[PDB]
Length: 270
Ligand SMILES: Cn1c(-c2ccc(N3CCNCC3)cc2)cc2c(C#N)ccnc21
Image (cartoon, rainbow, N blue to C red; front, side, top):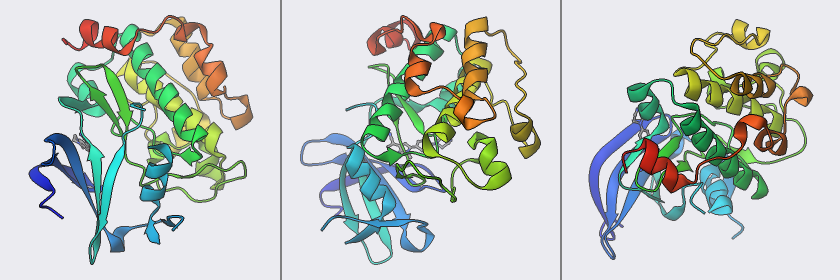
């Protein structure tokens, strides 16, 4: 039903589908209208009632402003339509880093803290995101709040071992590159290590499988000794040597984070 929603500009497209700017005309709330062709769907879950894309299962399990909320969804002959909340104004973290380069550690601390608190929510809901990166993080520029997006690559969190992966290869851990095996939490800490390096250096540290396997971090920007330690810790080659969400948020570099609105007034011109 596109009598219930008003379609706007095509915000973007790619491996996740095609997302449009939209408005729910009942109350004029800004929304996002995601389209997914059924033939391009990798993983199918099913609601407790019918066969849906696994993204719908995961979204309802985690649907809080750290994770984007799934509002409604429709089934078409050959596509699925998702209705997601849309902040206003927004800029995804990838564009934000492209325009401003390496971020101040106070800003990265706030951004990195919220993502930690955001994926902590996903795991508590039984959801593993499997594609943590700056492209999949939105910045609510008025409130200073980051929202996680794109659950089209995730899975139900499980304590056993994974053997499939349809996420971003430069963010995948070395155990996946060599053995095509990983555990969700430890692989998530690795990608969080890539994400933290990306924020403080302006670009990701690895581009080829050889560097992922070697696990040697070179810093191309001035980074505090504390932030380097936490980054290298998250990027430890053996998964069991990596920190836990608790060990990360107790780290010296993660102390005295700004509140989200504080972050917007100082760093986002709010
Ligand atoms: C999936 N998605 C994107 C989005 C995806 C990709 C891009 N970009 C691709 C990389 N180049 C910059 C543009 C920008 C926004 C925005 C949203 C929103 C919102 N509000 C809600 C749900 N889902 C979204």
